[PDB]
Image: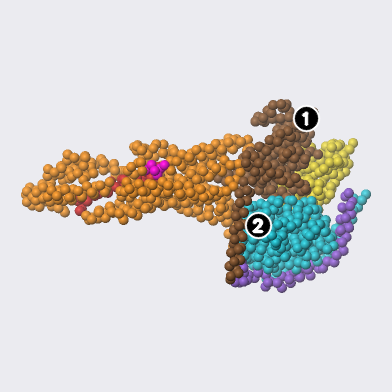
Chain colours: A red, B purple, C brown, D orange, E cyan, F yellow
Amino acid sequence: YAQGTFTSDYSILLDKKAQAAFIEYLLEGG
Amino acid sequence: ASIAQARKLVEQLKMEANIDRIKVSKAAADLMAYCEAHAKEDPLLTPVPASENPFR
Amino acid sequence: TEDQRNEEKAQREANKKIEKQLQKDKQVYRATHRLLLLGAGESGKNTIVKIFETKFQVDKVNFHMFDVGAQRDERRKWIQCFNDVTAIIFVVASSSTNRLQAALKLFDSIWNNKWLRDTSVILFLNKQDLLAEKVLAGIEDYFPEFARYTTPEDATPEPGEDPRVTRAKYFIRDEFLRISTASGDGRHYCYPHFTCAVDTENIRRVFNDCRDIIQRMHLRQYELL
Amino acid sequence: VMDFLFEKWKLYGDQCHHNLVCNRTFDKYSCWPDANISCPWYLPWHHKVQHRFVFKRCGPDGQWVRGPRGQPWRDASQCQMDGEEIEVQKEVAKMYSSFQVMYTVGYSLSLGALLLALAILGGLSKLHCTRNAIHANLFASFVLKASSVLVIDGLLRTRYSQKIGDDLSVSTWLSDGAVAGCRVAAVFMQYGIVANYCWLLVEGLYLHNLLGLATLPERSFFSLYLGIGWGAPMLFVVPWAVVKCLFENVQCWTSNDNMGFWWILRFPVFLAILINFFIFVRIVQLLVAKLRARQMHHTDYKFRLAKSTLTLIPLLGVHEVVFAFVTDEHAQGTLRSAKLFFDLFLSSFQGLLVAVLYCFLNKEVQSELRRRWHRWRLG
Amino acid sequence: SELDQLRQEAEQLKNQIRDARKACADATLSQITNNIDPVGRIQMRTRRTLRGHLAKIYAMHWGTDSRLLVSASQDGKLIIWDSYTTNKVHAIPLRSSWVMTCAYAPSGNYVACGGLDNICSIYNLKTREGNVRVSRELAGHTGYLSCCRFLDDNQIVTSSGDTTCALWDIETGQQTTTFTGHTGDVMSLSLAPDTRLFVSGACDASAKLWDVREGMCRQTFTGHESDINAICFFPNGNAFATGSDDATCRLFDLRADQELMTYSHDNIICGITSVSFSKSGRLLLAGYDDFNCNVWDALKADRAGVLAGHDNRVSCLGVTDDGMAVATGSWDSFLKIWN
Amino acid sequence: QVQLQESGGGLVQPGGSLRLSCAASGFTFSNYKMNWVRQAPGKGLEWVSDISQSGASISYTGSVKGRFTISRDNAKNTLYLQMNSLKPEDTAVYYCARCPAPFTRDCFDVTSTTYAYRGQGTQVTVSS
């Protein structure tokens, strides 16, 4: 499944980069 | 019987050779005269206004 | 204004009724095969059918065969009417003033005609029994290349006849396939059959060739052939 | 899963406040009574740092430690995420961005080719032609999926490229209204994928039915094909949307969490490919039979035409069988960076070569263009 | 020894006519019309397109009211159109699917058609039952019907592929007069404005002028190389134009008894299927096998325009009695009205 | 006026040689494919040979192939048929036939129903 699987995998990856950045905000910056 | 067709052809050719033929210049002048006398009444040469035109 | 209201209303209703019939008989027109039955002479032409129209049906498919009656032998004009038929059934008396060359020249004109370049030809080679009798008793003089022709490898043995008949009748079939292949290909095709005046199963052969013609047309439109 | 992290942090903030040298203060990360404190449980990697500790001390009465820049707490080294996991995810993030650029070109090139192909098809003699009416709807399904994929990917980049600098900034980011536009584009993306394989099936069904008849099809039946092409996808997308809205209403409806709900979208896609491969084999058998017929006496050039007339692969969309040799379940591992790149390459460029092969390389279209070219060049 | 002498005598009469025609040739029509204002490029647009025929269109004809036209298609149909509103007034079925010609009565009460059945069928359009029914079938031709033209509601002249034209009496269904003399199939005919003479173009590359009342050939016009497909009369009735398979059109004058002008171009190699003049007689429109129709300045032999909208062979072409519109049918089963 | 006049013919001994000439006028010679047809006594019209417009394509009936040769000269508007080894089976009237239309490969011209673009015919008789 070319686009259905990639969009799901790209969306999970982006979500984990959002969680990572959230902890970064908690540590420093804010 | 090819003679009957040949004889009929010769008899028919007599009538065509006995006619009176006008000059080509005279015959070609009348066609030119007719076309210039009806040029205004020709919707394809001089297009009519769209109001008086049922296809447009 | 009132008069033009009802006249336009009535005229639009009359057109609507007509278009309902025009779609109803468009379905019949598309689902019917139209055929031209053509013969260079006697050739036993009235044996495939058994004056101007004959309808038959194979496997719930309607065929519309049109024999040519009181028309003259000047075919150059009325033959353009049949450029949209499915196929032209060309009937040849294989047992032949050298009527075999006349049939070859007529097939050459039909094949190469400007408007008949999309129309396929179904070739029936009749008088198979009469051809067998003549060669056994004695086309050698009419075609000087006959005594140079070998029966093709992909030829049906046809049990019950000596190879002399098979070589002679396949030579005549290759004369028409020489014209059929030395000219336009892909747009129209030739289907030669060795018919004989004993059985009327040629109706099945016309059905099979008409199905082949339609399938090749569909594949041709999709650029698959 | 980002919603779960925020809620877990909300519980932690309430937990310390409910419970509540130097005094007791709760910072954004953790809190201490008025070091020797375990890592907070709201961290998504709390399992790996279960035994770890947070080392902040006071000693003298001066501030907390030294208040270096913005009164931070320092340490956060034993509870820090593993570098190997961060490094591999950064590499995966780079690879996906390269692929995303690769198919953005393919979809944009396909969009240009298909819109140009629709104009030529819808602007010449062959208009009622059901062959070009099936193709025109097929082209509009490629345009419908290329657009929907570009829209959802553009929305995804904007949504996750923002920055948080306020406590309430995260709260409004997770709320509805900022995602409702994304969820509509998610439903429009899934419809375009299914409706593209339902028009790939109509191409097979129409051509399979043409070649089985002995005569012309009497009537075009071009109302059932519109129902299959455009109406059949809604039979599967709508039950997917409601289940996604009821059971997996997390963020934008793009991540697949429960694969059971994912199978109600790839069932009309697996079915279309399964049927069109049977039709593909049936048509190729017909082509071989006609090529090998003694009518035109093919001599060693039968293979060239039989190989060339496999431009039926982009029409029937059967190229997906070789790439998807394994069910998507547990289909992850070393088969990356070559299988995924090629699979995205074929899907994004499939609209381009469908328009090229069936609207630009077509003999009838080229002849019509030449006739229309000479007609114009008359003053 | 009679066959040899008859041929020699015929040639003695043949070249005598050539000398008589050559003697009367003083100046060409080009010389007299050399210093006249050219028409200029003629721009015509497809105002309306009539669709509804299942197969190729072989013939069409205009009504005298210049609004209704009948068209014959080889799918077995004969449709009557309202050109102004593009509405099918009638769509009648034919017994034979191979119809090669159609005519419209000057009164507008009757319609005719014919083809490979060698029969002309007259249809009553004003039947008291409200439906159009065949009222007569004229039999007696031994070849396909090529053209037919009403003189009244009671008389009609039909050309046939048996090298013979005929005058019919519809009330009795009997062939009043037979016009023999052509060698090949007669492909077209055109009635004079007074309908006392008509011209016929055959496949022997010649045309003939017939006297309807007497029933004998008056003049024979040669000059074409191949079969003549179309023929039309000049509006004043003293000339006519013919189109042939040698990719040319020619204008013949009855009084001069000689070809006047040739309408040919080096880029045209296909034959002419249809020929018609304009209201004034200045434009000669000719349909071609190259799918487009050409407008010709009849006095200067300069192509003044092109009608190109048909996807297949242009089979029929006619101009209204008021000259307001031109209708062209073709083998793509579509009619088009041009202004 | 399309006119085709044949010149030649006569009585020759078996095995002799003869040449026929077909003078053409009234049409452009180069645009048409020319033919040769004959009519033996008691039989209908039979096609003998034809030559294309350029002269590159030539065909013969099998009864005369190897003996007769056809040639055209697009300067004098003439058509030739050189005949060699005239067996007594070649006694016939030879006509010069022209295909109905220009620039075409088709040809419908063997008809006895007074085909138009055909010559008068020269009688070629062979006897011992």
* Amino acid type, callout 2: Ala
Q: How many marks?
A: 2
Secondary structure, magenta segment, majority class: loop
Q: Residue furthest right?
A: E1
- Residue at 77%, 57% (x, y): give it: E158
Locate residue C83 relative to residue D242 in the image: left or right.
Answer: right
Tag 1 residue: C133
Q: CA distance from mark 2 to mark 1?
A: 56 Å
Locate residue C174 relative to residue F48 in the image: left or right.
Answer: left
* Amino acid type, callout 1: Glu
Tell whether position E220 is magenta: no
Tag 2 residue: E91
- Residue at 55%, 43% (x, y): give it: D209
Locate residue C41 relative to residue D246 in the image: left or right.
Answer: right
| Secondary structure at numbered mark 1 | helix
Q: Which residues are magenta?
A: D262-267
Label 2 marks a residue whose chain is: E
Q: How dense is the environment of label 2, judged by Cα within 10 Å: few (below 14), some, or many (20 and up)?
A: many
Residue F118 in percent (x, y) is at: 80, 49
- Residue at 70%, 41% (x, y): give it: C89
Q: Look at the picture and state if E49 lies above or below E36.
A: above
Q: How dense is the environment of label 1, judged by Cα within 10 Å: few (below 14), some, or many (20 and up)?
A: few
| Secondary structure at numbered mark 2 | strand
The image quadrant of residue D297 is top right
Q: Is residue D240 visible?
A: yes
Instruction: Using the image as rendered, state which of residue B32 and residue C85 is in the foreground.
Output: C85
Label 1 marks a residue whose chain is: C
